[PDB]
Image 1: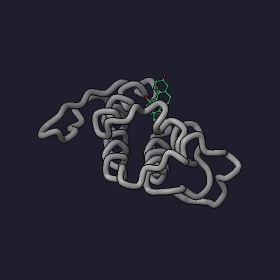
Image 2: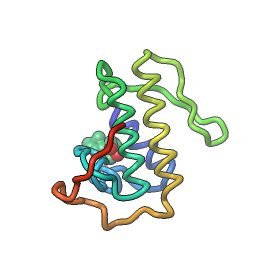
Image 3: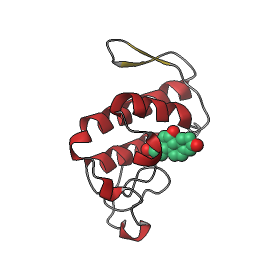
Length: 121
Ligand SMILES: C[C@]12C[C@H](O)[C@H]3[C@@H](CCC4=CC(=O)CC[C@@]43C)[C@@H]1CC[C@@H]2C(=O)CO
């Protein structure tokens, strides 16, 4: 679920998901169109694609369980949807973490009309 993803992001990165990632670039949060701005946005693009791979799943509302093994995120057994959503969210949180070094506040609240360019999942 969205609140769980938010917590996973905070855990990984130290940033609150709202506002650091909820409106970032062309793909994070509501939004996704055009060319991603940066690596972090590309995380969102791939995450968007990841959710798109699951049209009869509801990742905002569906709660999954995960644990930590070494500080590593380990998705735990639920429904097939929950398992898959968990893996999507886990990847995105790790990707944010991997790309904190190029996170740019200038992409927060990024204007929709600057998102043109195209990209197939
Ligand atoms: C889902 C995200 C996690 C997080 O918890 C946010 C969400 C945006 C909307 C939202 C509404 C809430 O009241 C709870 C948090 C949450 C539902 C965030 C946008 C950034 C992050 C994403 O990157 C999605 O692209």
